[PDB]
Image (tube, rainbow over all chains, first blue to last red; front, top):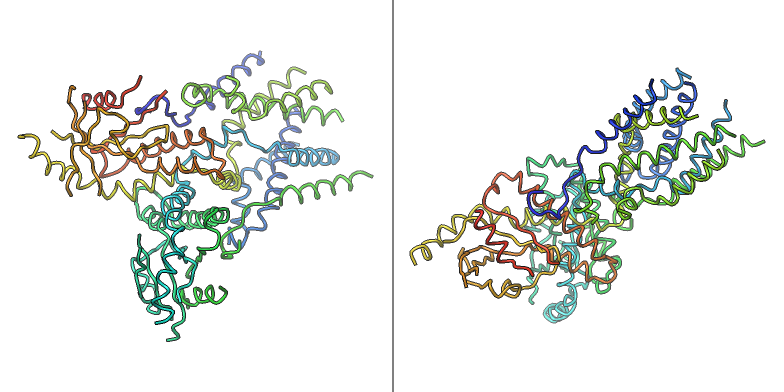
Amino acid sequence: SSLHPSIPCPRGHGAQKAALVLLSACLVTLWGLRYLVLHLASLQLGLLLNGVCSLAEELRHIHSRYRYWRTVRACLGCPLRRGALLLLSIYFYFTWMLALLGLSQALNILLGLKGLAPAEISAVCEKGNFNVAHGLAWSYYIGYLRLILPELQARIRTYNQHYNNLAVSQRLYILLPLDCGVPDNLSMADPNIRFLDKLPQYSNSIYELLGQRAGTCVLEYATPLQTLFAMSQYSQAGFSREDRLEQAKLFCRTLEDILADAPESQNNCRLIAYQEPSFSLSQEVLRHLRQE
Amino acid sequence: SSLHPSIPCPRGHGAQKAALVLLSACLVTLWGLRYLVLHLASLQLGLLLNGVCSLAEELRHIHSRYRYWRTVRACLGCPLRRGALLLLSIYFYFTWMLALLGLSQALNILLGLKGLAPAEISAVCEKGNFNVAHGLAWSYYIGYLRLILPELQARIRTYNQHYNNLAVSQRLYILLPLDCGVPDNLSMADPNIRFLDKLPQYSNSIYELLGQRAGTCVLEYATPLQTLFAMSQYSQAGFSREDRLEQAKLFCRTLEDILADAPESQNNCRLIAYQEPSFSLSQEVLRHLRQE
């Protein structure tokens, strides 16, 4: 780190080299077979059973996360290497071994052997530097919404006198396109959506909603979706559109869990997300206003 | 997920319950010992050796990451449970077993058994929702610096005519306090630092640097450190100040690696970080200007 000494360096090839050197030195020290086979076969059988136990939970998230082969290929990692090692173990090969092996796997799952080392958690979290979902949520909450949300219904009640007699719904409505393609103009997504007013006091937009003119909405896009899209159109990132969709979904759920527990943001903003494959933004927004 | 069906739900207690049920059903099926002991003792010995091999790499990051007992306690996790299991295995207990065990650990380290399942990577990354370091870096790069950095030396050469004859250094200098406490005024951190000018064209600040007046700096704080600090002063977060320091260091290194590979941002901005425990911002900045 050519900046400051207290800032740590990324993790290098330290464990592999010294580990191989020490564990080869012990081999040469003790240099000048069926227990080995049973041990490694039991190891791979336990790892495969652990993968099946993880797949038992990941069987639920099919339609919402993984859209079969891709699910198992993502949950067990590389099952080709595991199958090849299993065929080598069975070829170079006692049914009561399976009972104690299953009990060992049950004890390791329940008692929590699979709780990782915190150094491993750090090496996973600091890898690849594209884990962009929580910075956007906390920045969008602290930097924008926390400031604008206290005075919001006050300035709505300010505006309502000029439309009730001559109204505006009380909840702020945020659009969250999962395409991550955000135009500048909200009339450009639908001609039924027209600009009506700018709310006085920074930016706000009060809209009419359609010829059945029914809704008076306070509407706004979410901001960091454009940041995700510029990361997508940044060529040297190597940031795929599937990664964009993944981080968009995680951003949505994170912002939902933040607004679920906010003390001043309980019943004054509501999130609405959509995704195109026939479609209408206006019908979904009107469903939210009618259910309001 | 009460928002949209395609947004996935957090991972629940699915693996534990069904795994325990199935692995107890197999026990009751096969219901109506020293191999077990050797297998589990070999398991814990291999896990302990793997922890030592990880500690061999994590021995380097003492002064920069971990400031001994805390290092091992963070690298091996809970060694009390491992020691208790090791004493149970040795109590309820062949030196040539150690050679094959070490060779098994060497093969598992080198060939890459410890490459995790991608579902495990997802469950680690989606846990706890305080991994706030990359959203801030990419938002601060795309949203602010990418726009302001092309025209920067042009407007510096615009300004230089009024001070060379009557200068301004060419690199933008960013302060990065690791305290994450950012005052509004840069003269409030040091009376030697005085406001000289606002650079015409959004915000910019050209400063004199001290009675030995020597430096003409274009100076600015980094923005999301205030976001980190407001996360620190948010009471319901449970966000400790050590977590704040950790995410600040990771933010610094991430922004450094982004600016290392930027195509238009090669030699026009330089990062400077500092940390208080006698101190001077001005002396460190002047060292950077003299080495310039």
